[PDB]
Amino acid sequence: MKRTFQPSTLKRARVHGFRARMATKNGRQVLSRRRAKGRKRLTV
Amino acid sequence: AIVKCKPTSAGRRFVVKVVNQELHKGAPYAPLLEKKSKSGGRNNNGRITTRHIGGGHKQHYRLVDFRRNKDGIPAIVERVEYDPNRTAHIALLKYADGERRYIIAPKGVAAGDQLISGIGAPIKAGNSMPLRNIPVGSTVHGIELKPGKGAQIARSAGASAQLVAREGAYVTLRLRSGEMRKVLAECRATLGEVSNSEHSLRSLGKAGATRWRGVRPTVRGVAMNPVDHPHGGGEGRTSAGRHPVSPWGLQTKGKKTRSNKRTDNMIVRRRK
RNA sequence: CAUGCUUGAGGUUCUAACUCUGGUCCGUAAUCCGGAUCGAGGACAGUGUAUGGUGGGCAGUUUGACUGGGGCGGUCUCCU
RNA sequence: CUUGUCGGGUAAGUUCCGACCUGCACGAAUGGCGUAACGAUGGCGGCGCUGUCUCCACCCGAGACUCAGUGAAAUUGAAA
RNA sequence: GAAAGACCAAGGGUUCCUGCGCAACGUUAAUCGACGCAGGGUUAGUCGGUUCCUAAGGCGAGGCUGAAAAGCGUAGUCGAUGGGAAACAGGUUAAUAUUCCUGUACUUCUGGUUACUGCGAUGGAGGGACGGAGAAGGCUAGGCCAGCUUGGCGUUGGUUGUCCAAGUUUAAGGUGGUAGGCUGAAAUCUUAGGUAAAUCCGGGGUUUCAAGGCCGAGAGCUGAUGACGAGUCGUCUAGAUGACGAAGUGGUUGAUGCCAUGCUUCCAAGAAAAGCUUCUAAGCUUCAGGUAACCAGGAACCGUACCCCAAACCGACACAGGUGGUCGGGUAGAGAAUACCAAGGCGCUUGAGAGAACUCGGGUGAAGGAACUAGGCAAAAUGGCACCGUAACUUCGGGAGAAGGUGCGCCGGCUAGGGUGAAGGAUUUACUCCGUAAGCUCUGGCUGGUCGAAGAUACCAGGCCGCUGCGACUGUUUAUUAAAAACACAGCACUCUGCAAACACGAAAGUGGACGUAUAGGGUGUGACGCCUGCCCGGUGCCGGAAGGUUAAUUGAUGG
RNA sequence: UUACCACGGAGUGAUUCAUGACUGGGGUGAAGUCGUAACAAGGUAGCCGUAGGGGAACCUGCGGCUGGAUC
Ligand SMILES: [Mg+2]
Ligand SMILES: [Mg+2]
Ligand SMILES: [Mg+2]
Ligand SMILES: [Mg+2]
Ligand SMILES: [Mg+2]
Ligand SMILES: [Mg+2]
Ligand SMILES: [Mg+2]
Ligand SMILES: [Mg+2]
Ligand SMILES: [Mg+2]
Ligand SMILES: [Mg+2]
Ligand SMILES: [Mg+2]
Ligand SMILES: [Mg+2]
Ligand SMILES: [Mg+2]
Ligand SMILES: [Mg+2]
Ligand SMILES: [Mg+2]
Ligand SMILES: [Mg+2]
Ligand SMILES: [Mg+2]
Ligand SMILES: [Mg+2]
Ligand SMILES: [Mg+2]
Ligand SMILES: [Mg+2]
Ligand SMILES: [Mg+2]
Ligand SMILES: [Mg+2]
Ligand SMILES: [Mg+2]
Ligand SMILES: [Mg+2]
Ligand SMILES: [Mg+2]
Ligand SMILES: [Mg+2]
Ligand SMILES: [Mg+2]
Ligand SMILES: [Mg+2]
Ligand SMILES: [Mg+2]
Ligand SMILES: [Mg+2]
Ligand SMILES: [Mg+2]
Ligand SMILES: [Mg+2]
Ligand SMILES: [Mg+2]
Ligand SMILES: [Mg+2]
Ligand SMILES: [Mg+2]
Ligand SMILES: [Mg+2]
Ligand SMILES: [Mg+2]
Ligand SMILES: [Mg+2]
Ligand SMILES: [Mg+2]
Ligand SMILES: [Mg+2]
Ligand SMILES: [Mg+2]
Ligand SMILES: [Mg+2]
Ligand SMILES: [Mg+2]
Ligand SMILES: [Mg+2]
Ligand SMILES: [Mg+2]
Ligand SMILES: [Mg+2]
Ligand SMILES: [Mg+2]
Ligand SMILES: [Mg+2]
Ligand SMILES: [Mg+2]
Ligand SMILES: [Mg+2]
Ligand SMILES: [Mg+2]
Ligand SMILES: [Mg+2]
Ligand SMILES: [Mg+2]
Ligand SMILES: [Mg+2]
Ligand SMILES: [Mg+2]
Ligand SMILES: [Mg+2]
Ligand SMILES: [Mg+2]
Ligand SMILES: [Mg+2]
Ligand SMILES: [Mg+2]
Ligand SMILES: [Mg+2]
Ligand SMILES: [Mg+2]
Ligand SMILES: [Mg+2]
Ligand SMILES: [Mg+2]
Ligand SMILES: [Mg+2]
Ligand SMILES: [Mg+2]
Ligand SMILES: [Mg+2]
Ligand SMILES: [Mg+2]
Ligand SMILES: [Mg+2]
Ligand SMILES: [Mg+2]
Ligand SMILES: [Mg+2]
Ligand SMILES: [Mg+2]
Ligand SMILES: [Mg+2]
Ligand SMILES: [Mg+2]
Ligand SMILES: [Mg+2]
Ligand SMILES: [Mg+2]
Ligand SMILES: [Mg+2]
Ligand SMILES: [Mg+2]
Ligand SMILES: [Mg+2]
Ligand SMILES: [Mg+2]
Ligand SMILES: [Mg+2]
Ligand SMILES: [Mg+2]
Ligand SMILES: [Mg+2]
Ligand SMILES: [Mg+2]
Ligand SMILES: [Mg+2]
Ligand SMILES: [Mg+2]
Ligand SMILES: [Mg+2]
Ligand SMILES: [Mg+2]
Ligand SMILES: [Mg+2]
Ligand SMILES: [Mg+2]
Ligand SMILES: [Mg+2]
Ligand SMILES: [Mg+2]
Ligand SMILES: [Mg+2]
Ligand SMILES: [Mg+2]
Ligand SMILES: [Mg+2]
Ligand SMILES: [Mg+2]
Ligand SMILES: [Mg+2]
Ligand SMILES: [Mg+2]
Ligand SMILES: [Mg+2]
Ligand SMILES: [Mg+2]
Ligand SMILES: [Mg+2]
Ligand SMILES: [Mg+2]
Ligand SMILES: [Mg+2]
Ligand SMILES: [Mg+2]
Ligand SMILES: [Mg+2]
Ligand SMILES: [Mg+2]
Ligand SMILES: [Mg+2]
Ligand SMILES: [Mg+2]
Ligand SMILES: [Mg+2]
Ligand SMILES: [Mg+2]
Ligand SMILES: [Mg+2]
Ligand SMILES: [Mg+2]
Ligand SMILES: [Mg+2]
Ligand SMILES: [Mg+2]
Ligand SMILES: [Mg+2]
Ligand SMILES: [Mg+2]
Ligand SMILES: [Mg+2]
Ligand SMILES: [Mg+2]
Ligand SMILES: [Mg+2]
Ligand SMILES: [Mg+2]
Ligand SMILES: [Mg+2]
Ligand SMILES: [Mg+2]
Ligand SMILES: [Mg+2]
Ligand SMILES: [Mg+2]
Ligand SMILES: [Mg+2]
Ligand SMILES: [Mg+2]
Ligand SMILES: [Mg+2]
Ligand SMILES: [Mg+2]
Ligand SMILES: [Mg+2]
Ligand SMILES: [Mg+2]
Ligand SMILES: [Mg+2]
Ligand SMILES: [Mg+2]
Ligand SMILES: [Mg+2]
Ligand SMILES: [Mg+2]
Ligand SMILES: [Mg+2]
Ligand SMILES: [Mg+2]
Ligand SMILES: [Mg+2]
Ligand SMILES: [Mg+2]
Ligand SMILES: [Mg+2]
Ligand SMILES: [Mg+2]
Ligand SMILES: [Mg+2]
Ligand SMILES: [Mg+2]
Ligand SMILES: [Mg+2]
Ligand SMILES: [Mg+2]
Ligand SMILES: [Mg+2]
Ligand SMILES: [Mg+2]
Ligand SMILES: [Mg+2]
Ligand SMILES: [Mg+2]
Ligand SMILES: [Mg+2]
Ligand SMILES: [Mg+2]
Ligand SMILES: [Mg+2]
Ligand SMILES: [Mg+2]
Ligand SMILES: [Mg+2]
Ligand SMILES: [Mg+2]
Ligand SMILES: [Mg+2]
Ligand SMILES: [Mg+2]
Ligand SMILES: [Mg+2]
Ligand SMILES: [Mg+2]
Ligand SMILES: [Mg+2]
Ligand SMILES: [Mg+2]
């Protein structure tokens, strides 16, 4: 049976990447919210 | 002519084809082709704005010349071609100094002809001139509305209009829809009617022939749920218990929708 | 009754406001956008504000109690 | 009402096919009445075939059973 | 064994190899491991990226729009799943190799020297450059057979021979311009065109010739007196090493691979841009730049281990699930079905017994033959090729493989055809034409004999028929209890819409409809086809009318 | 033992008789019911073909004929 997670490294970066979040001001709210809580990763 | 296929299959019984043996069957003229890509009925917000559109064959766009403003130079018809974008045929002209061009093919033009344009041209079918110097009572096609913009009216297969009256700087002509309209006499037109007038005798024959043209199935509103259509709902097979209406709530059995009010003076009398 | 200076509505016309998802010039190496100039319409259209009509397209809600289970029926205040 | 009544099919048919008209409460593009071909569509009837059945019998593998190793689960107030 | 074998891509990330280990992990033990510790291991001008080009789409200076955030979009510049330079064979490690080594190639750039010269783009032309189906060929890989070389003479009758086994290999490139496909060619005089120019492209006139020009598999030759090759010998220690090294040819068959982005045909009419060739503008002109020959030098950076239809990816698991593309041998066979094998891989990480009921998956079954049951559910049955034969009805295609029947193994006798192909013959003398005995290979015909219970013997492989309801048909649907009579459908009708269209998404700009134009576009119902579709405009909608009555903001006479 | 072949089997058609719930017209009947279509110019002249309509004879449209009276 086909499952929901089909990995793709290029599609992962283009939706959830660092430059994708920096493009819009709502993505930049996500990054500052994760810096405030102290996340080690901050982006995938 | 029209060709009726034999019932060798279940899907061939009711196919009636419009097969023209005079059409060119080589490649089109490449320097007058540009790419067009399908839209699916979606606008730049990505939303379906016109439904029942999708699929079909890949097509090039043919740069048809609707202005016909090479006045005074004679032309010759090289061939009549098939256009995926019209229901009418197109003709490849060759003017007296190179300059090949596509125009909408008139009814009788095949292989020679002269098809000159401008003032002082003869009154044979296929010639283009301003509406001032067109005899009253003649049949015209490819009518221009604004000077310098090109043909907009009477362009599909077998279309024509009648020049009925002439008075002042304007001129009145009866449209194929039964409407009397006044047009600026400076605008241009072509004599005769459009080719391929037998296009209306065809019969697609099967459901897959509609999908070849990029049309998707129509689901009727009485087959839906109340949340989808105003006609939806009911136990068993019902009949749209209200007055018939659009998916967005607009009456469709006789209610008028024209609300222009700016071009009203150009309408002599409506099509009713 | 005549004229005069006003004034409600009606019709016609003009061009100069406005409009053009019409042509050609420039910015420019550009089917965007501006400016210029021709052409068309024209005090209309259109937008702001005020107001009548329509409007399950959409919204927030209401739709009683008793009752030999509920519903249907009946009853709900006062006098003998 | 109803397994209406008559005919056919069966030894026997509340289902099936053909009719009658008393249509509780058919009916003409929420189409009426037919229709060759088509259907993992509904009903009924035949031929062949048979462990479906009278009515089960024997045989072959995998478990169940015993020995060695590893080792769960729902449940549970306490139980002479 | 069309995989349970090999190889790419995605995904993973050291799981790869070697020493030392067994606590935990491994559904049991483990000396073993995809497990623990420590070392090692991935080598490129040609492979894949990067660099060059663009598609859908994204972002978008200025701009237009919008309470703000922001939306749309022009110039532009990102974005492969596509376009665009060039390498093969052999050897080698415990682990890499088209990357290292050996041999033989190819592409592109830089700097010099010589010789001769009109150079120049972001702009113009050409080219790149393309659909579905189908059919005739030509060829190659691959497969068989024969010959050859080396070895053998068989635990049991025979086996020195029409006997047995193995091997009989070799690329890119260069040369060659073939089967075949497309196309008329040259000279000269001009020019309402290609936004300007143009010797280039396009258009026109005249003369001459009947021949050029462009693509194009493959053969042959050469690469290659070399590599490889069973094996033989010498040294070291059942194994390593160095040297040597046989034969290595002919015939048939033949692809779904190549010619082929070809050819024919049909409608649903079948990417862009760059690299590339050429023309010229602004500019140089005796610097620049260009074309040839020779000499010298260069080709950076990143990925290369290993799994990869799985125990390493997605499913919490060493999980009967899922996962794109390529290769794909023999005997039978129409076949990539099926069966038995090859190369290669594996026996699925608890075993041993014993042979109760009962459960699961199967085999056979007396006499009946649907009596079973809601219902022939399930099972049994049919099943191939050739020939004979086949009803109602019909939209004339069908129904139809209707129904039903006959033959089929093996060994001989006679006999008829096709393909390939020596010798010969012809002229265009050579990658050519005709034609060929034997050999090899593929189709048949009529005549006997013979064995068994049975010859389509296994696997494989339609059950058929008669009345009716529904839906015309092929299609679609409730991922995970409903596949249908439901949805769609071709056809039919009503209605709206004159183009800045109606309509839809958007506070708006704008976008779709549509680079469409009433034979068009939207909505609504019905649902192939045949015969038809009757009466009612009182209600509620829609359409037309404008006389009269009622009637909003607004204005403000009059009165208090 | 083979060849020929009668009886008898199996499958599927054609044709022809009898019969069949129920249905369609026709003929013959008697002092029945409704009308009055034709024969006179039958009181709207009749017939012929075709189409629609109607309790029924029949009516109406289109084309045709005189086998139509007055004149
Ligand atoms: Mg998920
Ligand atoms: Mg921050
Ligand atoms: Mg068809
Ligand atoms: Mg192009
Ligand atoms: Mg539609
Ligand atoms: Mg189209
Ligand atoms: Mg069609
Ligand atoms: Mg439809
Ligand atoms: Mg609809
Ligand atoms: Mg519909
Ligand atoms: Mg439904
Ligand atoms: Mg529904
Ligand atoms: Mg919705
Ligand atoms: Mg609703
Ligand atoms: Mg229902
Ligand atoms: Mg109902
Ligand atoms: Mg319903
Ligand atoms: Mg628009
Ligand atoms: Mg106004
Ligand atoms: Mg107004
Ligand atoms: Mg307003
Ligand atoms: Mg509602
Ligand atoms: Mg609502
Ligand atoms: Mg509500
Ligand atoms: Mg509330
Ligand atoms: Mg509530
Ligand atoms: Mg209340
Ligand atoms: Mg209560
Ligand atoms: Mg009660
Ligand atoms: Mg009580
Ligand atoms: Mg009680
Ligand atoms: Mg009580
Ligand atoms: Mg109680
Ligand atoms: Mg009943
Ligand atoms: Mg009954
Ligand atoms: Mg009965
Ligand atoms: Mg029964
Ligand atoms: Mg029955
Ligand atoms: Mg019945
Ligand atoms: Mg009844
Ligand atoms: Mg009904
Ligand atoms: Mg009706
Ligand atoms: Mg009904
Ligand atoms: Mg019916
Ligand atoms: Mg189907
Ligand atoms: Mg279906
Ligand atoms: Mg049926
Ligand atoms: Mg029965
Ligand atoms: Mg038993
Ligand atoms: Mg057993
Ligand atoms: Mg034990
Ligand atoms: Mg135990
Ligand atoms: Mg197989
Ligand atoms: Mg295997
Ligand atoms: Mg494998
Ligand atoms: Mg990876
Ligand atoms: Mg992982
Ligand atoms: Mg390791
Ligand atoms: Mg290992
Ligand atoms: Mg070890
Ligand atoms: Mg131990
Ligand atoms: Mg363990
Ligand atoms: Mg263990
Ligand atoms: Mg296990
Ligand atoms: Mg390890
Ligand atoms: Mg772009
Ligand atoms: Mg943008
Ligand atoms: Mg900006
Ligand atoms: Mg780019
Ligand atoms: Mg790529
Ligand atoms: Mg590519
Ligand atoms: Mg490429
Ligand atoms: Mg390896
Ligand atoms: Mg090398
Ligand atoms: Mg170009
Ligand atoms: Mg391509
Ligand atoms: Mg083609
Ligand atoms: Mg093709
Ligand atoms: Mg061979
Ligand atoms: Mg020998
Ligand atoms: Mg022996
Ligand atoms: Mg012996
Ligand atoms: Mg060779
Ligand atoms: Mg070669
Ligand atoms: Mg040739
Ligand atoms: Mg590697
Ligand atoms: Mg590797
Ligand atoms: Mg693999
Ligand atoms: Mg395991
Ligand atoms: Mg697995
Ligand atoms: Mg798959
Ligand atoms: Mg095979
Ligand atoms: Mg098969
Ligand atoms: Mg097997
Ligand atoms: Mg085996
Ligand atoms: Mg093996
Ligand atoms: Mg196991
Ligand atoms: Mg059993
Ligand atoms: Mg069983
Ligand atoms: Mg069994
Ligand atoms: Mg059995
Ligand atoms: Mg037995
Ligand atoms: Mg038995
Ligand atoms: Mg028996
Ligand atoms: Mg029987
Ligand atoms: Mg029974
Ligand atoms: Mg019983
Ligand atoms: Mg039962
Ligand atoms: Mg069954
Ligand atoms: Mg059975
Ligand atoms: Mg079975
Ligand atoms: Mg079976
Ligand atoms: Mg039948
Ligand atoms: Mg048969
Ligand atoms: Mg015998
Ligand atoms: Mg049969
Ligand atoms: Mg049968
Ligand atoms: Mg019936
Ligand atoms: Mg029924
Ligand atoms: Mg259906
Ligand atoms: Mg169906
Ligand atoms: Mg039907
Ligand atoms: Mg039908
Ligand atoms: Mg029907
Ligand atoms: Mg199909
Ligand atoms: Mg089918
Ligand atoms: Mg389901
Ligand atoms: Mg379902
Ligand atoms: Mg189904
Ligand atoms: Mg199901
Ligand atoms: Mg459905
Ligand atoms: Mg629309
Ligand atoms: Mg329409
Ligand atoms: Mg619609
Ligand atoms: Mg329907
Ligand atoms: Mg239907
Ligand atoms: Mg339907
Ligand atoms: Mg129907
Ligand atoms: Mg009304
Ligand atoms: Mg009325
Ligand atoms: Mg009105
Ligand atoms: Mg039979
Ligand atoms: Mg029969
Ligand atoms: Mg008989
Ligand atoms: Mg009879
Ligand atoms: Mg009878
Ligand atoms: Mg009787
Ligand atoms: Mg009469
Ligand atoms: Mg009378
Ligand atoms: Mg009379
Ligand atoms: Mg009378
Ligand atoms: Mg008379
Ligand atoms: Mg007659
Ligand atoms: Mg008559
Ligand atoms: Mg009529
Ligand atoms: Mg009649
Ligand atoms: Mg009448
Ligand atoms: Mg008539
Ligand atoms: Mg008459």
Image: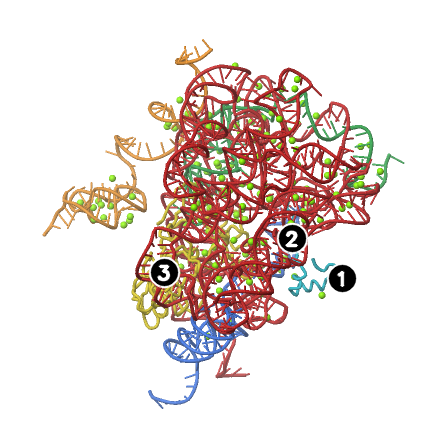
Chain colours: A cyan, B yellow, C blue, D green, E red, F orange
Question: Where residue B71 sits: x, y (%)?
Answer: 35, 68
Vertical placement of residue E459 versus B203, above or below: above
Q: Amino acid at mark 2?
A: Ser
Position of the C terminus of chain B, as image quadrant, is bottom left
The residue where tag 1 is placed is A38
Q: Amino acid at mark 3?
A: Arg
**N-terminal label among 1 and 2:** 2
Query: Residue D44 versus residue E122: which sits nearer the camera?
Result: E122
Residue B176: which disc? 3
Quarter location, residue E345: top right
**Is there any visible trace of residue B222 in the rendered image?**
yes
Q: Disc 1 and disc 3: Cα gap in Å?
A: 74 Å
Query: Residue E557 versus residue E172: which sits nearer the camera?
Result: E172
**Is there any visible trace of residue B161 in the rendered image?**
no
Query: Residue E316 versus residue E387: which sits nearer the camera?
Result: E387
Mark 2 belongs to which subunit?
Answer: A
| SS for dot 1 | loop
Residue B17: which disc? none
Residue density around tag 1, few if under 14, some if 14–19, many if 20 or more, within 10 Å: few
Residue A8: which disc? 2
